[PDB]
Amino acid sequence: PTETERCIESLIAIFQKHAGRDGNNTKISKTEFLIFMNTELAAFTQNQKDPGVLDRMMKKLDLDSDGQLDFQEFLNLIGGLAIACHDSFIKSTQK
Amino acid sequence: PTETERCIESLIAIFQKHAGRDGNNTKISKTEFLIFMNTELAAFTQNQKDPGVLDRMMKKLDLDSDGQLDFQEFLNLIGGLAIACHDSFIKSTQK
Amino acid sequence: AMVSAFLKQAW
Amino acid sequence: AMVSAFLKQAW
Ligand SMILES: [Ca+2]
Ligand SMILES: [Ca+2]
Ligand SMILES: [Ca+2]
Ligand SMILES: [Ca+2]
Image (cartoon, rainbow over all chains, first blue to last red; front, side, top):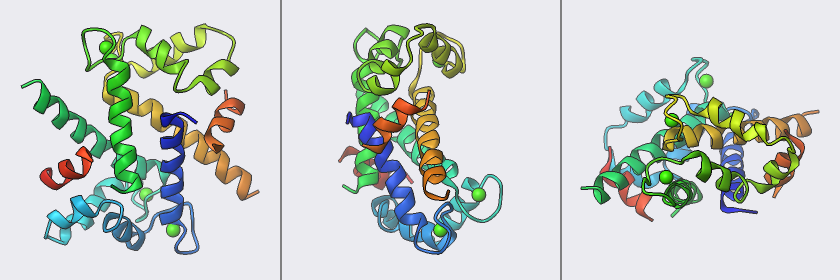
């Protein structure tokens, strides 16, 4: 598998591992998003000290407003972070 | 780094490696997309035998229609593929 | 892995 | 890697 193939597969596995803690593995609930954010994204999470931030991220990512994140909504989180990071890498090297 | 962190970083590296063949490393041109598709995504590409398919994918992904893919447009390709793959994994296991 | 096979089947 | 540090700085 290529690196792109491997990363597509990891995305799927990470979602599934975090979405399968309760009885619905197709949705990440608020509790599961809390755990994902404090363990896969600990570094970004620990910085922020206001606990209302995750509640605000959740609402913002929950596009159909059912209170849970489905795979696609979770991908918009991954993508939003990779875009900010890529913007900083450009900013830092074409300065 | 977590698997999510590593995958965000690989996304950025893959884009940058494929976008940096010509003099613009912030955009993947048509030629570079051709190479990326025949090497990172060879398995999906080789199946299709109609060469007009990539031209049609390119047009579809090129949302601001400047003829090149920027990082975000490239992420919509990665995401569209991970979503179809996750849909097939659900279809196959909740059958 | 599973993705590479999927990609082969889908499209 | 670079991402983890970025995440620390951004937000
Ligand atoms: Ca769940
Ligand atoms: Ca939702
Ligand atoms: Ca380029
Ligand atoms: Ca474009």
